[PDB]
Length: 405
Ligand code: HEM
Ligand SMILES: CC1(C)[C@@H]2CC[C@@]1(C)C(=O)C2
Ligand SMILES: [C-]#N
Ligand SMILES: [K+]
Image (cartoon, rainbow, N blue to C red; front, side):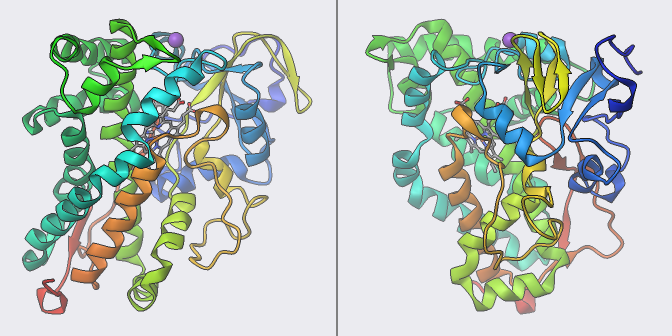
């Protein structure tokens, strides 16, 4: 239901947006969040949904808030409060100065130099998945590619068996888009239950995989603790299993619906990187936030110590103040402004991996299956949460229009 309005919040600022089930969800998840940017809606509103919390609705305030870690702390970054309180992943639950030492370690496992180590495997897996599908003339995109492609790359990098994917993917989904079977804290404890013996094993007998690297790592010249190792590795599983998986489906849904845009990339494949950036703006999908460390007046609004504020990464690039005609996809857009990978000191470490996976998917799919569409009569359903997503994506094509490479 709606939580009682706290005394410090003016009634004129209330807008009861539900981030886990927004009212306009049938029109598409980005469209549903974009209701927060309609002419009647203030820059900063309070929703009584999900325990009650602020929402910044415009890219200027979202950016400003992500920059100001002094007032807007990452200690409690998820809504609802019980999720944000339980949330203890590293580095994401930490503020500078303490956060930074852990970033460098995490960067060692998921950063640009590891994208180079994985380059050929990424390329090979994309091609082999797509070639297997190509003659079928149809697929369920979410299960047949969007999941297996980034997840199998992640499980390889982490040296975890592919048979563990259904369990880990269930747990990860409960943290970002819960179905009600588990609280965030239960899902977290089950993820840690999984990781504890693995971290033990790999500190005793280190391998080359990402878990071994983290668990035997140093932070600013000193040994990482077992606890600390567990809390990153937890973060890495979540990051490996959810965002790219969902983003791929938004992108491919759009391409299936937009022959002109597919055409553009088939005829001008050099535009694929710019196209990746524009889709990252248009189909942005993350929304977490921060907790107020003290009473603070922010843009004429009185925020109180301990208030949660949702700072939707998704909204900055959709803000017409940042990008003209923001719901239009324009691969030639001159300045693509977005905060899809976050903003400030927690800027996504995985972004170089993500872009590689997106760019590879677009190139290799369009090479083999240039001409495809949504299955006739299918209605595509989205789901909203910390990371929003696509429930299912049935595609079809004529195998006669495809090319085995
Ligand atoms: C399209 C795909 C992706 C999107 C949209 C995305 C988005 C984000 C966002 C918005 C944050 C910041 C959260 C905050 O400020 O509270 C973040 C942090 C992070 N991401 Fe990603 N991400 C993607 C892919 C990945 C991948 C594939 C990995 C793993 C290889 C990854 C690893 C991380 C890590 C380790 C952090 C934490 C950095 C820190 O807290 O200092 N991300 N991501
Ligand atoms: C909000 C995020 C995208 C960011 C990386 C994974 C994620 C789900 C987090 O818990 C922090
Ligand atoms: C990041 N996910
Ligand atoms: K916490």
